[PDB]
Structures are given as structure tokens and as C-alpha cells.
Amino acid sequence: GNRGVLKVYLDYRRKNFNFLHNSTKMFLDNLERVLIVTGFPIPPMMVAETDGPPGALAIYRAVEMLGGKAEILTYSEVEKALEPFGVSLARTPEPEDYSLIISVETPGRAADGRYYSMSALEIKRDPLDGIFLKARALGIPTIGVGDGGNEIGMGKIRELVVGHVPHGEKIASVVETDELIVSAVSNWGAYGLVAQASIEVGRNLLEGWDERRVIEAISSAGLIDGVSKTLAPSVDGIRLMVHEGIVELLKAVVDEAIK
Ligand SMILES: [Zn+2]
Ligand SMILES: [Zn+2]
Ligand SMILES: [Zn+2]
Ligand SMILES: [Zn+2]
Ligand SMILES: [Zn+2]
Ligand SMILES: [Zn+2]
Ligand SMILES: [Zn+2]
Ligand SMILES: [Zn+2]
């Protein structure tokens, strides 16, 4: 129940009614070698959180089911966490190397060049948005998912963030992405991408996704809850039940269309 981002969605979707469909389409048309990027350090521990990795993983799993290849660029602690899922890690990634670069909950620099958390605490850690500024310049397909306004891709709608989101002027990221997905919780944004791509392809790419398994797993591995900054199996302060609810609802929707 976060009011600012809810208002940014109404504004955004209102003028870009088809962002999810356009996003899903760019995705489906550039599967050859997809670089997926996640990991949001949380001040002051600067430890990544549970929002982002789950979604990146679902996209990765989906990219492979479709026949493409995916690698993940993220932080150390997330690699450990995502380790049980046998995910290919990116090694000295170069934009030129991919056909598409996605971002699920990743700090995007602000207008002042620095990085900030929803609480405007500066993030001090090596950035991961650079490759996006480069991807953009080269014209490589780029997609970004966020739920607050300080994530890579949110630069596409800074006016909206600055207007409805607390600390906006300072927090808002200037990094833009070709397509942008905004959702209450980024993971859910990635799941939407997968559900939309499922309807488009006629296969439910989300069938089998175990929300609970993944949250608990990565929470044990060390990834924290962004709001409680604790080690609870939750993402952005919402507990597993609601999250499973949304994933099960997305699955239902995918089927309804496919079948
Ligand atoms: Zn407005
Ligand atoms: Zn280059
Ligand atoms: Zn505040
Ligand atoms: Zn966020
Ligand atoms: Zn989040
Ligand atoms: Zn279509
Ligand atoms: Zn968060
Ligand atoms: Zn259920």
C-alpha cells in the first residue's frame, strides 16, 4: 500500500497504455543473448535485497524456455543466493555482446550522479547501471523494471517520480531504458513480463514457479528485506502470502488466454 508509486503508475500507464505489451515484444524479438541485471544495495549495510533477484531469475528461466541464452550481472551476495538455481554469471560483460539488456530493481544514478535508496541514503558501492548508458548509446534493446523511481529505466519518467514520490528530486534516476515496466513490487513486474510473453507464445512460462521456494532460499543465502532490513522471507515488507497470491493470479491469467 505505497501511495506515491501507485500514482506514478496511473500517470504512466495512462499515457503509455501498452508499455507491458511493447516491452514483452522487444523481449521476444531479442532472445539471442540476454543480459539480466539485478541487485539493490540497502544502506547502511549495502547488502542487496530480496526484491529483484527472484524476478530476474524468472525472466532468465523464461528466456531459456524460449530458446534464448541468458547470463546474470549482479552483486556477490546475490550470486551466492542464486547459486542453487544454476544461473550463468556474466564475465566482464560488454554491451556489444548482447541482443537485449534487462534490469530488475537496480540502482540508477540520480541527477547529481549519485545513487540513493528510497530513504535518500546514499548508496556506496560499485554501480551496475553503466552498461545501460552504453547499451542505450549503441542502440541495443534495453528494458528496465522498477517500483520506486530510483531504478535503472525510471529516468524515462522522472517528471512523474519527482511529482509523486517522496525525495523524488534527489532520488529519481536519470537512467532511461527503451521500455519500462512499473509495478508495486519489481519482482511482480518481471512476472508480468513472463506472463505477457506466455500469452504471446501460447506456453505458460510461469507454470512451476515456486515463489515461496525462491524467497526462502535467497533469504537464507543472506539477502535482506528492503524495508525491515532484516532476514525475513519477505520482499519490500510484504509477506509470502500476498506474493504467492500475485504469482498464482498471474498464472491463472496466462492460462485463461492461452487456453
Ligand atoms: Zn500525477
Ligand atoms: Zn563498447
Ligand atoms: Zn522519507
Ligand atoms: Zn525500488
Ligand atoms: Zn521493491
Ligand atoms: Zn500482441
Ligand atoms: Zn525493495
Ligand atoms: Zn495459493
Image (spheres, rainbow, N blue to C red):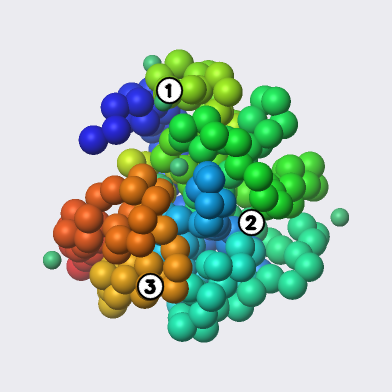
Dot in front, 3 or 2: 3
**From what the image shows, is residue 166 above or below residue 113?**
above
Dot 2: element: strand
Q: Name the residue under label 3.
A: 220
For ligand 3, tell me if the residue under mark 1 lies within 8 Å: yes
- Of residues 188 and 140, the one nearer the viewer is 188
Give the quarter of the image for residue 154.
Answer: top right
Q: Callout 1 environment at 10 Å: few (<14), some (14 to 19), or many (20+)?
A: some
**From what the image shows, is residue 106 above or below residue 108?**
below
Q: In this view, does 105 lie to the left or right of 192?
A: right
Q: What residue type is labelled 2?
A: Ile
Measured as percent of width and height from the top left, residue 100 is found at 64, 58
Q: Mark 1 or mark 3, which has the lower sequence index?
A: 1
Q: Mark 2 points at which residue?
A: 101
Find the distance from the CA under tag 1 to the CA under tag 3.
31 Å
Measured as percent of width and height from the top left, residue 53 is found at 47, 62
Dot in front, 1 or 3: 3
Give the quarter of the image for residue 76.
Answer: bottom right
In contact (CB < 8 Å): disc 1 and disc 2: no
Q: Which amino acid does label 1 sit on?
A: Pro
Dot in front, 1 or 2: 1
Measured as percent of width and height from the top left, residue 184 is found at 33, 41
Dot 3: element: helix
Quarter in which the C terminus is drawn: bottom left
**From what the image shows, is residue 143 above or below residue 122?**
below
Find the distance from the CA under tag 1 to the CA under tag 2.
29 Å
Residue at 63% x, 56% y is 101
